Image (tube, rainbow, N blue to C red; front, side, top):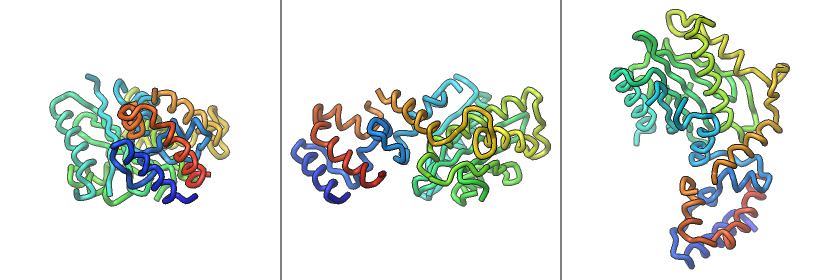
Length: 270
């Protein structure tokens, strides 16, 4: 069986059940289904990233001073992220927000993190890509259309992964740590300096924790990311994934589609 063979079989079942056919089998995959079958190389999609946000306490709660957005780049390639940064800058002017955390899909299944803080009239930004130091043009173009100065946006990336499949979780690990570094800098642990650059070394200390030669716990090895995947998957228990919407719309169809999805997972992500 091939991926297209599986897709044709799924689409026959969807047709019999008066549901919309799909164009890619990934449309019906989600982190919980993959993790329940021990496919830990599954790349997290946009719908999975909403559940991961709740695991890292981002969806809300960290009404409060922090803004949060899951967006993408690549209408113009920049409109969604630009719109989020604009809405944030308005809320800063309204006195409602101090900080924005954005988790950004840069197109080819790659997730990166951008955190912007406002402190007494200035906007400082910190960008992290788990692949290591390189910033993406659409990100830079979104920042330029929102008048965030390039001098005040800093690439704090550290080499953390090469496999690619865990960049979705690394994006949240890095957002947590950038936000902790900013929090501690506000309390005097470090100084921002004129352009916000002063905290970059402290950020990189947290981003490098538990990888390579660093012995700090948790060691963020493959087993660590398997357990994070298991923990994120527990939050799925429905309507927020395309799979969950199909199941709720056609209860019991999972008995016909899940065997084929498992075959696809074995092929795409062995």
